[PDB]
Amino acid sequence: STPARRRLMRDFKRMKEDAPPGVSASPLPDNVMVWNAMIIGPADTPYEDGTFRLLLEFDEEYPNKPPHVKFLSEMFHPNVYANGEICLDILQNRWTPTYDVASILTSIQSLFNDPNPASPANVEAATLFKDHKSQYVKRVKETVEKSWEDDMD
Image 1 (cartoon, rainbow, N blue to C red):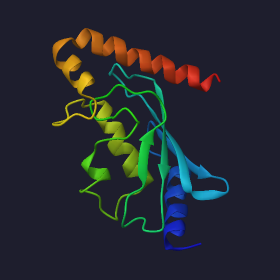
Image 2 (cartoon, rainbow, N blue to C red):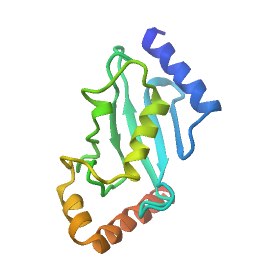
Image 3 (spheres, one colour):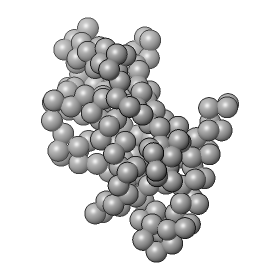
């Protein structure tokens, strides 16, 4: 046990009891440095009800240094790259030691309700969102279903 690991244990208590709406996460029973998480596609978005899973990997510099966060589920969002990585200042240059798993998950959750990034990670998704919003939704619906098939395996 170390400062980082204990902090992570505290982040876990908060998720066990006061877990924010639509977000859930938990460390492996044997390794607190690796966590699995899931964000339910928010309300009135084409992402609605999708079970999007992520992988968070921490180190001993936490919470001074953020964890590596990436989506394991196939995604179609202007802020999410092809390898599942996310473009979000909170996770990069704007990170603060006050953040925790909960806040990380909520901040990412919020992106679903605002596909308006300045500089997109997924350019195809950004363009389609502006030009052919009908197709964007069709594509987003496709990933929502795909997230459901994953669980069935």
